[PDB]
Amino acid sequence: MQYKLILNGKTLKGETTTEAVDAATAEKVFKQYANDNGVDGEWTYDDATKTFTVTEGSHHHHHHMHRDSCPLDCKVYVGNLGNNGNKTELERAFGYYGPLRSVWVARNPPGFAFVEFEDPRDAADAVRDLDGRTLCGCRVRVELSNGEKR
Image (tube, rainbow, N blue to C red; front, side, top):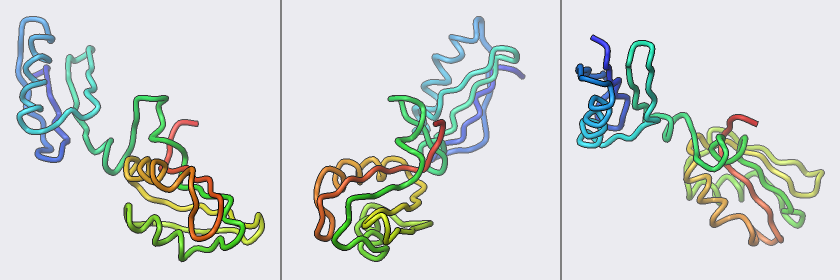
């Protein structure tokens, strides 16, 4: 017991194992075992035991990207709301793209906020669709995710 594909995906969470001639004829088939389940995870691997792992939870309830190494940036952030900036308008402007675990905004600076989604990708969609524009009655700027490495 060695060449050990820990599944932790949408579908199945509970490993499977095999053994092979090189531990790469193992990968190249673990690849398809997990792609049949519906996973591409982290694709992590270990060489000291020749174990593997696919933790797709790292794209759902923890986070990553392939741009730097954070999801996007450290939290949800808003500013330039200087004509209006309040919690309610942002609670529900972000509420559309996903639910909020946390929310807050300053009256001074004139219209600056911060919030918490967990998801990094509906957060990147609020950068796609709520940054660069106008929210409520302003000339916005906006930045979102939840983490992680800066």
